[PDB]
Image: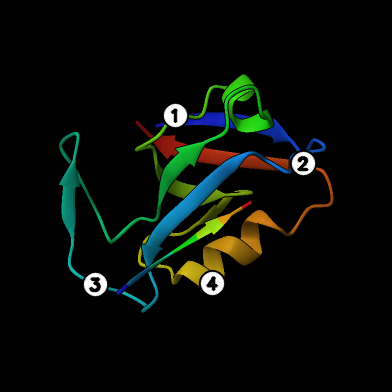
């Protein structure tokens, strides 16, 4: 269970 | 391990971070050393701040702003990245 976020 | 300073620009820091949402996990060997799970850089915007600072896709994020993030949740790492208004210091494993 991964998540990806643009910063 | 290498330390990179990134200055937020009009496109933000210009990278994506990806990794586990939970806390902890099993140790993994990276370059002969053991670490708990690391978030990683899943995208780098060409010409953005991270690119210009030398961050590359696949870099594993070991520290954010001097804080070790082994086993950290995705939220913890995103929050640390967002801690500064302009400056970000990453320690990465390429």
| Displayed quadrant of residue B15 | top right
* Quadrant in the picture for the C terminus of chain B: top left
Q: Read off the chain for label 1.
A: B
**In the rendering, which numbered label is found on residue B25?**
3
Residue drawn at the location 29% of the way across and 60% of the way down:
B37
* Residue B64 in the image: above or below residue B73: above
**SS type, badge 3:** loop
| Displayed quadrant of residue B25 | bottom left
**In the rendering, which numbered label is found on residue B56?**
1
Q: Earlier in the sequence, mark 2 or mark 1?
A: 1
Which x, y percent locates residue B2? 46, 28
Query: How far apart are labels 2 and 4 at the CA level?
Result: 19 Å
Please report contact status of discs 1 and 3: CB closer than 8 Å, yes or no.
Answer: no
Which x, y percent locates residue B52? 63, 20
Depth order, front residue of B51/B69: B51
Please report contact status of discs 2 and 4: CB closer than 8 Å, yes or no.
Answer: no
Q: Earlier in the sequence, mark 2 or mark 3?
A: 3
**In the rendering, which numbered label is found on residue B75?**
4
Q: Read off the chain for label 2.
A: B
């Amino acid at each position: 269970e991964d998540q990806e976020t643009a910063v | 391990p290498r330390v990179v300073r990134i200055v937020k620009s009009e496109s933000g820091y210009g990278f994506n971070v990806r990794g586990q949402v939970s806390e902890g996990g099993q140790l993994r060997s990276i370059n002969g050393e053991l670490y708990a799970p690391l978030q990683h850089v899943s995208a780098v915007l060409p010409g953005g701040a991270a690119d210009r600072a030398g961050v590359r896709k696949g870099d594993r994020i070991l520290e954010v702003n001097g804080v070790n993030v082994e086993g950290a949740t995705h939220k913890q790492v995103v929050d640390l990245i967002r801690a500064g208004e302009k400056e970000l210091i990453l320690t990465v494993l390429s």
